[PDB]
Image: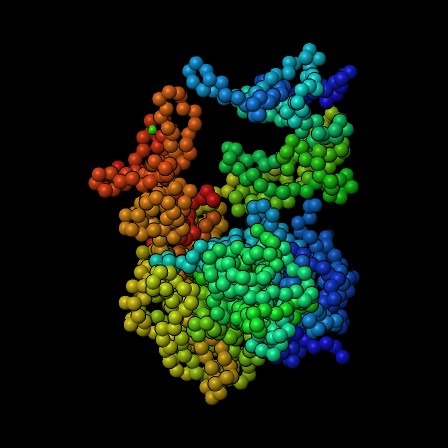
Amino acid sequence: SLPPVNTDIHDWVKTKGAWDKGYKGQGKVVAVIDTGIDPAHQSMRISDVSTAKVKSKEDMLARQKAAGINYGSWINDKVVFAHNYVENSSAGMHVTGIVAGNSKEAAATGERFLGIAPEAQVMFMRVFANDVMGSAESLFIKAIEDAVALGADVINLSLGTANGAQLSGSKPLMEAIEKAKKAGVSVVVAAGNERVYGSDHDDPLATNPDYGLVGSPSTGRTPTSVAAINSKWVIQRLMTVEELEKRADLNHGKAIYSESVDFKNIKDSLGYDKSHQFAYVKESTDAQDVKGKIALIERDPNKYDEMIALAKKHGALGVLIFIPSAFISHEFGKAMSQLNGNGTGSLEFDSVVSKAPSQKGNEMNHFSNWGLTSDGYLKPDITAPGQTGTAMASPQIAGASLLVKQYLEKTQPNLPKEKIADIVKNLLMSNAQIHVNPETKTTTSPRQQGAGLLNIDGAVTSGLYVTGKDNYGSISLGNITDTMTFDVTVHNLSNKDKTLRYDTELLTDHVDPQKGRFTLTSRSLKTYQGGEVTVPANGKVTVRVTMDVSQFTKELTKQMPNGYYLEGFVRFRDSQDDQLNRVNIPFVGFKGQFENLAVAEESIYRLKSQGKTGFYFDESGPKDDIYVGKHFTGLVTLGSETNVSTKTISDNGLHTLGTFKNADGKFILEKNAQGNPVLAISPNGDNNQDFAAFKGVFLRKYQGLKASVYHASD
Amino acid sequence: FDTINGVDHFTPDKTKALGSSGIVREEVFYLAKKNGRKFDVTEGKDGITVSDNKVYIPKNPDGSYTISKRDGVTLSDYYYLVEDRAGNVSFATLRDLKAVGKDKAVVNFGLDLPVPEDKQIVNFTYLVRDADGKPIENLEYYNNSGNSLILPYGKYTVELLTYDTNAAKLESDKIVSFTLSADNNFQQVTFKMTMLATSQITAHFDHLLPEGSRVSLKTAQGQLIPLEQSLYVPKAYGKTVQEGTYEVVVSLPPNEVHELSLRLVK
Ligand SMILES: [Ca+2]
Ligand SMILES: [Ca+2]
């Protein structure tokens, strides 16, 4: 009698297997720490308060008195505590809906949306940063402590800094998180949305492999660091064209269209019109055009509806070219058929959303943060479906953590509070499903996807989880050398011992050979068969994995001269049935010396003297222009003109030391008669080339930078 | 700010000099326009020189200053300027100092840090509360700074909400009381802090320790901080970062090569 359930994510993450065992979050509590909720929504409800953790406003008041918390309040049986920590005079409503939404009514599409943990109650701490991030740290700590005190079971933390370190974070925050772990509280945090070094410019160069950007505090040992995969399905307003209701390879003539920066946007459900002019230039038109001509994003004369230049790319790119005065566009398989039917026909833009298969479906989110920790550790930990990428994956893992913690509290009743949260993390990671990049048909690097895509069923059905030497769901080897060895440990939590056959897939980065840049795809070097082990019930067993990577050192070192990653998965299956007890553990090591990778980019002078060029350096104007405003490692000085008919009263500002203004007025790196540039200064006081200071393009986080001067004899 | 006849009379508070932030010199003046800008360039005998187009309003006997409403000049073109004994100067537009009514007062919040001006945490936030308790609402700011509130006479309390804890430490009380009244009509409350500085400390033993060795640091007092063995150079133990001067003890819960690198200046 209730509407059906939307299972776009539930079917993929396998939540049904958990619900059908009694695990829906009853008597559990998620604390969302975010920017704003509305506790009154149709989905903020629980069924049967008699089993909730917090059974009444009076219960809540009791806990607040006990914990010593004189602010905020209980709202309903769902949002049992809410408070503003930025008190001096929605984004995180989606996250709450995702962890714990339990709606009786249906939504826009006809179906009812249930979160991962529909019977969880919720606590809401409004916290965010305003001017100097890190000032908010104290309000976040007060929030974490209150979640812990009033009795949260999971904390969904909205907090990130880009290129976090695992062991060397912010002392008071990392400690408050450690107290949260000691209270049995899983702490889930988005990985981040900056993706890799230089993501806004180009792919990283093959000589610079420390390109990770995962953010603090998800990089901490304790928190669960969630990366983001794109959902297979989208729910959005489509665009229909009725002469095409028959060609199902086009969602029955319903297009996903996009726009960029809001030129003159849409006017819904009215049978507008347009025909096809694919000659992009001066055709006899009477006003759909293929942006095949990748020239410039200039929309056409008055009536637009552009379509993709690259068959099946289905990027539907943001930024409308392949001001205003029309509207945006951009799909393709609908274009090269919309352009059939005589030249043109009639369409309209729907006003009620629809489900439709995703254009980027089953692909890692472009912006989900990647790569190692700033100090060499393997994060993020796990992937879920989701600039709000990882931020929507994070609550999936928070809800999963509620469900698995339930499983543990039932079937391991005496497991101690100080040790349950890690087991929740470890079961989730070990039972995740390793992703395969559907484009390149090869395994996605664990630096991008962690221990794999979430699998809630596997985690609450197999009694297995996997572990490395350091006793963690994943393996950070360190430096690697031609022969990789590590010891894996399998744990069994069922009361019947299980036998597993296990192999080892090995991966490195794929590198574009014509451009000398990573492609941010992985390359599968070899799979190493590894034998068979029997995991005693209520026990553990350790095997050793050993690989000889000697055969690859020539080619990989040649394309990645400062070291490369060797990473991958040790995958266990059931010995008799290929599909039972699928568990695995990711590992990454670095064939080289990670702790020694170059910190600054090579100096622009040296680079020019090898015909090379910097990673951010614009080779714009005249030959050997180095305009001080460009981006290079070099020295900067300050210049001032010598005036023969006045006292000069004006400096000329900074310029690249070694460059001089030329005829046109441009600073060129001039060379002396031996061929070389000349760095030289004259501390005479004239404020012309009196000092030299350092300007760097930094390839890695740094500290203790200082400048010194020695005699050249020295 | 009062009037006599056609008034426009600004009398500045008494500058209670006696000191290093004591005031030696004060001037009222207006900035005339000529050629479009509030400065001009005079070609002196030696070379070129630049100056604001100041015209000074003389100090009346009465202590006041007569803001004759005149020309195309306005109250946003008048300035009151002060120079202290160390030679820092401060100016304000007479419009901004007038924006505080006669029945109201000014409170100003700031950090007292023992460092110079520009190497200072310039960013923090606060909350102002009533005689009764409630936050202050309808904020009126003074002389274009976000830490100077204009509030009616009364008793109040201010709280230090947030500041850069990774750069400094609060040394004084977090919630300070202040009272604004007809005579005490400008209070300054400050939070003293001390600067934080960090070092990278590393103990680099010449030979690998036996597995599960616990390497630790002994603070000023008998405190001990645990060091974690680095994953990339297993001999190198010095992990932690807090700064101040230490000695190394290895338990099993024997070399040295100790190095701290002064690292700071974010
Ligand atoms: Ca967890
Ligand atoms: Ca000079």
Instruction: Locate residue A127, reporting x and y percent.
Output: 64, 53
Residue in front for this viewpoint, A162 or A468: A162
Q: Nearer the viewer, residue A360 or B229?
A: A360
Looking at the rendering, which quadrant does residue A55 occupy? bottom right
Which residue lies at the image location 51% right of the left edge and 75% below the top edge?
A433
Q: Residue at x 65, y 14 (%)?
A: B59
Q: Is residue A659 visible?
A: yes
Q: Is residue A419 visible?
A: no
- Farthest-out residue, front: A284
Task: Give the color scheme: rainbow, by chain, secondary structure or one colour.
Answer: rainbow
Foreground pick, A2 / A66: A2
Residue A56 placement: quadrant: bottom right
In the image shown, does A351 or B173 lie closer to the viewer? A351
In this rendering, is residue A69 above or below A666?
Answer: below
Pick the quarter of the image with the N terminus of chain B: top right
Q: Position of residue B125 (x, y in %)?
A: 63, 42
Q: Position of residue A94 (x, y in %)?
A: 65, 63
